[PDB]
Image 1 (tube, rainbow, N blue to C red):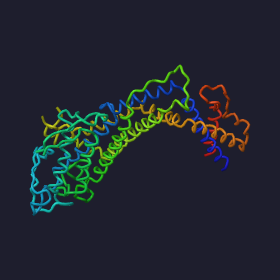
Image 2 (tube, rainbow, N blue to C red):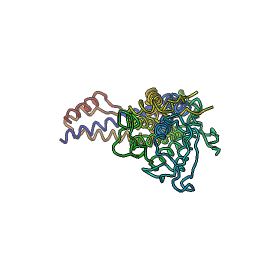
Image 3 (cartoon, one colour):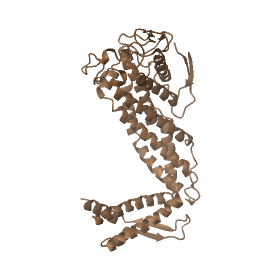
Length: 433
């Protein structure tokens, strides 16, 4: 009915009015502005300077361990690599050291198979093994022997230099590492080699891995369709968090507090508001992305994480952290998802202050226009009430008081009666039923 429609219409105007009002009041308070700026500076440093309690850093870590872990847990069952009949083609014949531990503990592989032609549903080309291996080796060297060598997101120019089996000169930074992680999964997915016996094995699942159930396709991209997909999105989301960290990083400098004793003019003294907004919007995105990484990771069945990744050949052969680089992968996937979820939960207080800082910053950045909007909303509500039955009881839901003495230039002080608002809010949900 038209009356129920009118109430939901008025209620949303009241909500919009109430919120814009609290923000306009907040925009005129240097204490409230100093608190929000101090909150952003603290949570900025907590996102880009910390490792353990940073959902940004832990988001990266899970994407890397999950990319290295997939490769470590199933590379052994990939149809023996090589160039095919013509040894001058497809990367030829090559040998790779420090590869993922196989079912016997072997860490050296030769891609010398000629009996089959490389490609999807067949063997993995030597060139694609070299590609995936290079990416894997960079990830492993970046984590180091301790598994903690990756610098905090604010630090992007730390050099990574080592010799493979060529000499690699790159950066130990999240942008480079996430690209390495993408190379592993993208190359695995497109090359889509065959899995020995079409993945058939001795697990309760019917395949070679617990939690991995064969749906009639024996190739790598068939068997691991869900896991490849979850990991690709994990990389995509954590990469978004890494881009947004540039914004946070550009705003990490400590500012001087506004004088609480002096009058603050919101029309003139808020030139800092634009970067304050961009900082808060970025911090909120980082959080969105870190949580999305959790959600992508949880598409992977629990049995595959606990009874395959946590029981992989790397742990079976005693390759752990703390010379040799065994810091990354399937051995630490399970604890990283715990550390990421825990870091997001511990970011609770900070997350709320970020949203509040964002809204205040947008209001300060657009004060003139936002204040005019408060007036429009007042006029819109007064108009809406006029046609309603018993408009007389409701007329006082909003009120305005003049103050031409205002040193801040806020000549009209707007108000809202919380009780008449509650009544409308509740009368609207009563009419909806």
